Length: 264
Length: 271
Image (cartoon, rainbow over the protein chains, first blue to last red):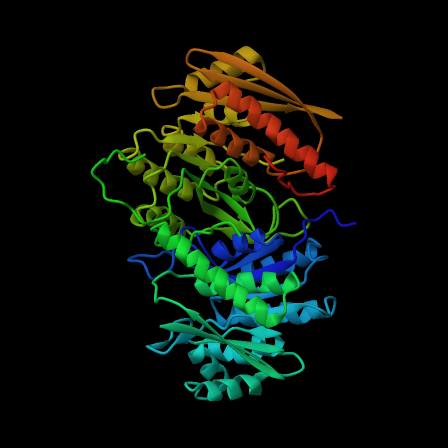
């Protein structure tokens, strides 16, 4: 009966004027799967910070809080089935996001919250706002149904060394709960490990080291789409991984420094 | 379009258009409707926001604001530094957040014009609603750079300070804005139930008029959509009047479709 626009997903992450990272790549990827999505920016950059220059910044708490609240006040969540989180600007955004999410669950008992704990890697460590980690551990993590950390991020979230697979698995297992259903850990091959309370599925893709950014965001985008379209978890992870590899190939064949989406 | 035949291959994304307007998390106004419409036409575009709102200020609540000058200027500068303008054929302007953004945009444009002689700068003089600052910014900075403008009667009067309450006068004012740079003026007036969309296309050598019938609606963004389809039409070979006519029909088509689905926000049907 609502006359408002609806969406299957609310994607909360970065946005670039130029480039294919955050919602700039996730939205069209999600659209490709035949799903609707409202994108809520956490940062608005001209391009990723990896280039010689970059401009823009974090979306003000008041604006950010307003964007989320507006989706409710506009009654545009009648079809909401998932909320994905990616690159966050500040801890304050995470706390606000968590509060918004806690509020939603009361009306969307089946809401699938998928969070990508973008914090960093092992080379210099945390390449995002220093206060993000604690914010993830305190407010957001407790709400996630699934998470997609890399080794370093799983270590920061669990406070456990995860260099060895068996160690990463135990760490991921220790995170599972009535709320947290799965942990997808990403590690010349790429290792993607799917962990649930009763299983562990290791997926290895022959991947070549690239400088292309946003693949993690593309990954999560294709993953949630698959889960929402009825794909079993592992299959959904594998397909997401394959779509990413495919896009990277298409992009390189296109001789482009930014991800370009081929048809699905 | 870059004239450097000797330029090496750029690996950056390329775009035919750079649309500078508002953006809404929820809704179909500004680039939120223009980008998808442009995409439908098979063109590429870079969206540079002037304001990032939760939705239009027409609803009961709305949040967000104007993009800071530093960010705004940076976004425009980044497009140059990323070398993503080799295919740039046009820059459209819509709702501007502040006069300072207009100055910043204009400076960026003057610079660009030097490397893109074929640049079609199309300006939509969004002034007014249902502030001295904005009108003057347009007159000093953007007006002297535009190749074409799409004002309604009120905006045409504001920019020129002339009375345009009759065909001849409206034409006269539009003609007065023409120059070696300003090639055309598209003035429209919604007569309000079945609102009539009166349109007058004015150039140095001709005057053409278009008239569409429209059902009264609260739908927002139709003007931004019109512009998106206009620039798209022009970039795909359509002659001015033909492009204006088609842009108007496409808008009507989108509005009907929107109503057909009983939506309070524009939704694009196939093209």
